[PDB]
């Protein structure tokens, strides 16, 4: 059973993502600690110390970026695991679908269907010859061109 | 043993449950995506140049995975539609067999020759009746004179 272990380790993935997130937020705490030192060094009349304070700040920013990249990598591998759980479930459902198709095709197959094909074709063929012959012989009895000509004449006096 | 009808009806809502899971593991990712959007929006205020690109990459990853989630969900739908039309095919087959049996046992009582005999007898009787009428009118109308 892969389902519970996938969930089991997903419970640890963001378990460590929260460790990473706290690691991050500590860095912005230190960045806020040092930004006001940059501010004060800017105001105290000599500006060239603020460059070294900025050296500190950009190092902290790089640390933040690296930690965020690590968290993103963790998220990506987690999503891959979830995707593959979905894929395995799809494969199992497809296997069951193949099984039910086997069960249904266990009933009828081509040869009985072909027997029905030819029996229906022959029966309808004889049927059509009987019906057409009957219609022709009943119409071999009374007029066609005349007996149609007054037909619309009968309709004309109705409307 | 289990009847084949039970297997198909079980597979129906089994595939439905698979769609259900796919729905859920989809739904979690839009929440994750909205969290990423909120984070990238709040973080872009202070700039910091680079980490925005990592978050955008993660956003694109989430979109690519919801793509596949929707794709497998659609695949399950096609499988369900096939297994559903399968029993319609079976029903067509059995009804066709029944109508063929009925029509065969029906036209087994009347064939080509005996109806042809009946029909020739009809034509002969119609000949006799029409000859009765035509000459009956003929001799007595021609017996009439001056008109």
Image: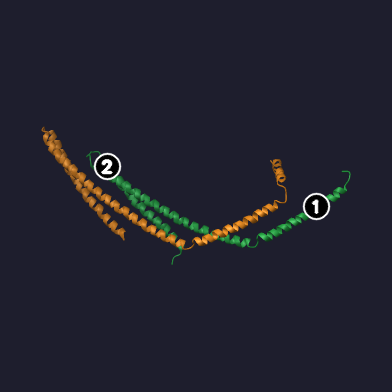
Chain colours: A orange, B green
Residue at the outermost right position: B146
Which part of the image, by quadrant, shows the N terminus of chain A?
Answer: bottom left
Which tag, 1 or 2, sits closer to the chain's start? 2
Residue at left offset 54%, top offset 60% = A116
* Viewport quadrant of the C terminus of chain A: top right
- Residue B72 locus on image (x, y percent): 37, 52
Q: Which residue is mark 2?
A: B40
Residue that appears at 24% across and 50% down:
A17
Q: How many C-alpha atoms fall within 10 Å of the one at disc 1: few (<14), some, or many (≥20)?
A: few
Who is closer to the viewer here, B37 or B86? B86
Q: Chain of mark 2?
A: B
**Compared to B48, does B79 lie above or below?**
below
Quarter holding residue B147: top right
Separation (CA) of disc 1 from disc 2? 106 Å
Quarter residue A95 falls in: bottom left
Q: Is residue A113 above or below residue B30?
A: below
- Decide: few, some or many residues near mark 2? Use Cα within 10 Å; few <14, some 14-19, many ≥20: some
Q: Chain of mark 1?
A: B
């Amino acid at each position: 059973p892969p389902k519970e272990l996938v969930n089991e380790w997903s419970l640890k993935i963001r378990k460590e993502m929260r460790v990473v997130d706290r690691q991050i937020r500590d860095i912005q705490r230190e960045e806020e600690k040092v930004k006001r030192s940059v501010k004060d060094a800017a105001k105290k009349g000599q500006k060239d110390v603020c460059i070294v304070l900025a050296k500190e700040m950009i190092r902290s920013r790089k640390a933040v970026s690296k930690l965020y990249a690590s968290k993103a990598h963790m998220n990506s591998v987690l999503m891959g695991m979830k995707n593959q759980l979905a894929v395995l479930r799809v494969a199992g459902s497809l296997q069951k679908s193949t099984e039910v198709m086997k069960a249904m095709q266990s009933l009828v197959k081509i040869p009985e269907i072909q027997a029905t094909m030819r029996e229906l074709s022959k029966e309808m063929m004889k049927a059509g010859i009987i019906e057409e012959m009957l219609e022709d012989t009943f119409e071999s009895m009374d007029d066609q061109e005349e007996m149609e000509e007054e037909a619309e004449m009968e309709i004309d006096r109705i409307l | 043993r289990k009847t084949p009808e039970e297997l198909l009806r079980q597979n129906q809502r089994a595939l439905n449950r698979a769609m259900r899971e796919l729905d859920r593991e989809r739904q979690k990712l839009e929440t994750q995506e909205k969290k990423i959007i909120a984070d990238i929006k709040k973080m872009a205020k202070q700039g910091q140049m680079d980490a925005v690109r990592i978050m955008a990459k993660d956003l694109v990853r989430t979109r690519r995975y919801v793509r596949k989630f929707v794709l497998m969900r659609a695949n399950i739908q096609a499988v369900s539609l096939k297994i559903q039309t399968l029993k319609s095919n079976n029903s067509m087959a059995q009804a066709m067999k029944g109508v063929t049996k009925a029509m065969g046992t029906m036209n087994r009582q009347l064939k080509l020759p005996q109806i042809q005999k009946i029909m020739m007898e009809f034509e002969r009787q119609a000949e006799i009746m029409d000859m009765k009428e035509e000459m009956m009118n003929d001799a007595i109308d021609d017996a009439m004179g001056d008109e």
